[PDB]
Amino acid sequence: MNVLSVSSEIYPLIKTGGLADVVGALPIALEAHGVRTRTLIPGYPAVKAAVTDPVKCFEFTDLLGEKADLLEVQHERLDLLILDAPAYYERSGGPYLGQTGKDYPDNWKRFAALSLAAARIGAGVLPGWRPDMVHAHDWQAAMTPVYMRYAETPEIPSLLTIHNIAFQGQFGANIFSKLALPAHAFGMEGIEYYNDVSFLKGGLQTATALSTVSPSYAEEILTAEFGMGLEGVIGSRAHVLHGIVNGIDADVWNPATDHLIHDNYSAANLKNRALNKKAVAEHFRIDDDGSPLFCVISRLTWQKGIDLMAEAVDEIVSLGGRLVVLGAGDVALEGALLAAASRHHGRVGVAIGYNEPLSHLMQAGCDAIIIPSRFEPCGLTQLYALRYGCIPVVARTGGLADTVIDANHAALASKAATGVQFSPVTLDGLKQAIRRTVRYYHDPKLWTQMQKLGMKSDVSWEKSAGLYAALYSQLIS
Ligand SMILES: Nc1ncnc2c1ncn2[C@@H]1O[C@H](COP(=O)(O)OP(=O)(O)O)[C@@H](O)[C@H]1O
View: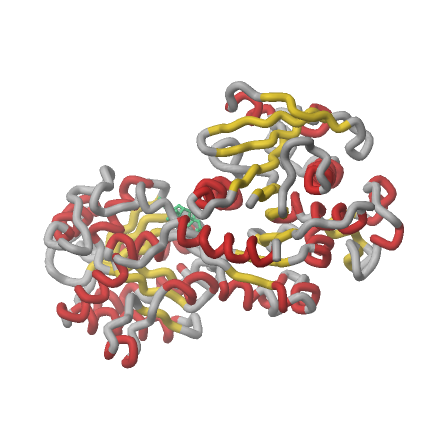
């Protein structure tokens, strides 16, 4: 099957957030499932520069009143379809922000044009290649299903994935007459959102199927706490809402080969793991012993529950454990953390900033990682931890609730548990989770078993991509 992906960004060409990571990894992974994907991305200056040997394969005479060439190029396993619309994308500034740091007043027309071109490509406008379906990503591309719906030619199936529910492509209804859409399209059934225009809302309304980055997150955005005002809409289409967990690069993240850790190991052979634990303590300048070593590797914010992690350090230390923290954020949280490091000198080590190699070493040498998030559409940290044999201790929120098998009586009895989850997401819940982890740690037969199992979890992109394929094939009937 041939799929047309649609996004305003893609790794490694352009990136402002995790959006590009998924859009850049899925297509490659999907090749393993027999799915050819061509990704339509804007001809950003940085895009045309990066790529090699581009081929003009089409020209749109009128794209909301603008000329555009369509270059097709293969870039590092990525089969791309670049949209060269100098009037929209030749700006020299972020893809969305001006040289001044703010949104282009043009944004609405810039991505509407990107969606419209995609809609036409989906309509068979390109001789030689026609998609069986389209997969749009986020608000920049959510208008693709809208233009297909209102186009004369019947729509082909569309899937819209929400990565960023907080960015809804909301604009004044005063741009409506410049969108090349029928008047009735400005309605409930269409793109009107409280007398304003909302692109995301439009696509949520028109797409054949909707998705996001975890089953649990798909449940959450149906509630007011996560829907960002869109829960009413999505809820009316819940019967076509899907949640699919993100994968990771399990070739790069493989403890058996990772070059950014002290010593390599595998589920089959863990002895070597302890050498990484030593190195982690040495690096953080803390005691090096056989006691539980917890880590945190995250942005220090209320969103990530690090407010709860600060009131929970004493509980760790009090239990005989250690804690090492790598991450940056809320200066009040940094401080309270830094302060914990002095009050519990030798037992708690904090490191503020960014450090990817250390991040690989911490996954390889710490015993457990605390991820007390209140918000986590999917999450990567717990997936790396499983892979690496670091037991995740996570809040039951979004992706975290979907990817860890909690060590409850039943799971331990069938030896199916891979980690510790807690809910609700409170300090009490957190201290409880922690205590449990330490109790588990002091039962080595149980602990190592949890590790070996977590380490055999398929957290690869291919696995994730296989779930998209099933859906694709299902949408394509
Ligand atoms: N302080 C840090 N140093 C190094 N890597 C980090 C740090 N904080 C997060 N990471 C890693 O960077 C990526 C982005 O995580 P952030 O935590 O930045 O993203 P998310 O939105 O997933 O929480 C993840 O792969 C995470 O493991």
